[PDB]
Every structure is written in C-alpha cells, then in structure tokens.
Length: 337
Ligand SMILES: C#CCNC(=O)CSc1nc2c(N)ncnc2n1[C@@H]1O[C@H](CN=[N+]=N)[C@@H](O)[C@H]1O
Image 1 (cartoon, rainbow, N blue to C red):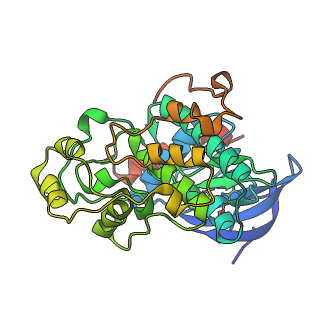
Image 2 (image 1 turned 60 degrees about the horizontal axis):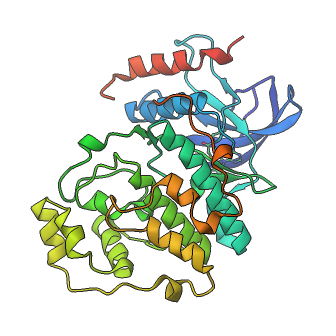
C-alpha cells in the first residue's frame, strides 16, 4: 500500500501526491480506470461521534445532489466489512485551486468576480431548493478548476432548513466559521434559515472585491462589532424584530454608528456589484435578498437564465457512533464490487 507524509486506495488509484490536510489529509492520484488525476481525501472518523456526524452528512448530501456547481463524489474506498473499516477515502474530481488560495495571491477582474458569484448562487439555488442549508460557505469551500469552473464543497455542517425553530437567546454558541457568520447568529438565531447562507455569500463577494475578509472578527462578540462597524446601527424597525430582551438591549447599549458606504470601502468595484452586496449584507434576515432574487439582480444579467439554473428533484444526531459507523458503511456500499 502507498504511504504519503498510510493511504490505502489501490490498485485503481496510484502515484499519490500530498495536497494538504484538514478531517484528514488530501492527496492527488492517478485514476487508472478513467486515466486522469483525481483528488482523494482520507477520513478517519470512527472514534469521535462528531467526526462521524460530519462525515455522514457530507456523504449523504453529496451522493444525492447532482449539480454542475456542487462537487460530486466519484468513488468511495473502504474495507469490505465494518470490522475491518477504519478509514474512508472520498474520491472527487481534481480541482486546480480554491477561492481561499486564489485570493491569497491573485487579483480578480470584475469579469471573474461576476462569473464566480453567478456560479456560487447557481449552486446555492439548487442546495436551497432541496431545503438544505450549507451553513459554512467561505472561500476555502469553493473549489475551482483550470478553467474557473466553480464547485461548492464541504457539507459537513449542513442541515435541513427549519425556520420555525430558528429562535434562540443571546450569545448562543455556534460552530460554523466566524468571519462568515450573519449578525443574527450572535443575537437570536440558530442558523436554521436560508438567509444564513446568503449572508456568507455577501461576505465572499466583499472579499473577492478587495482580497481581504470584510468582517475579520477575532472572537465571538467581536464578529458582531465588525459587522456593525460597517453596516452602522440597526434601525428601530430592525431592532423591534428582535424580541429577545438581552439581544435587543445589547444593541441599544452601543453608541450610534453610521453606515460606511460600500463605494468608499470598494472604490474600484462595479456599482451593480455593490448594490447586490448591500442586499446580501442586510442586517435584518427577513429583508435580506433570497438566492433566486440575487440571480435576477442586474449585476448578473450576462449570465441569468432561470431555465438553466436547475433545482433538486425533491427536498431532503444523538446517535452512538456504532450506529453512525454502520450508517457510513451502508451509505458507501454502492461503490463496492
Ligand atoms: C477528495 C475529497 C474531499 N474534498 C474535500 O474535502 C474538500 S478539500 C479539497 N478538495 C479538492 C479537490 N476535489 N481537488 C483539489 N484539491 C482539493 N482540496 C484541497 O485540499 C486542501 C484543503 N483540504 N481541506 N479541508 C486544500 O488544498 C484544498 O484546496
């Protein structure tokens, strides 16, 4: 068996190269059936029930989705029996880079920003049409190939939307990446509505315009104060939508902050881009633009075509890992001989 930097994927996959790490490690490899290099991630989740959760979610959702702007699973490798199954290998198309790596060193043209945003929202339209929330959209979860085709990846924190149960108290702990969290997560939201993903896309759009995160909070409440430092103080109407007193009185305790105009923050940006940015980065999640409205926005008019923006055929844990291991074993059976 080949070893990189204990990789067990043969004999279909050979000539492995390290790519990176972070629930395991990712390599590229030659696929001797399809005669092309692919990406393989090795996952070792079965001890920690948390790992088994994220792994099962990603596998289940990505095997059910089929969309040009969502990464597919080509193959899954694992032992023939549960007893012998310690690692799972996920095989995907090899993608040249991701948007995080790209924004570290490349300035994007406006034409690239517009194309990337279109593809992000086209993929998100399909996700949301399945009643799924991605819940961790950020640059490193947007893969890009050599021709800038964009595919959303990593559904390990994804959930079925549940708006009726979205309310919670002030300073409720949250897992998804801090810089891309909508302001209501810190105030009164569990992140169970589609508007959580639109906020994240707004943050991605801002970052494409300047190559720097727009709201780089250094800790939990600091995130909210970066957001308010640009958006300014919420209106009386938007406060009145927050019924929870601890959250509301926190906001009322802050000094008045004026809005920072988007065209002062991004003086080179296309004005239509900044109009759509404003609508994605709206404080009140009920007033925030939805995915299909964003696709119809004038910034995207070169690409918008609802007939070519498909939706899903149908919509979409306390569990002891023994049942989760078993669930993972079952979900991955279709790739065995
Ligand atoms: C197989 C499988 C499961 N795929 C994932 O879980 C998403 S990661 C990823 N998928 C890639 C892909 N299909 N082609 C090229 N490169 C990829 N990376 C890169 O692997 C290091 C980050 N790892 N992390 N998290 C960085 O270089 C990422 O660009």
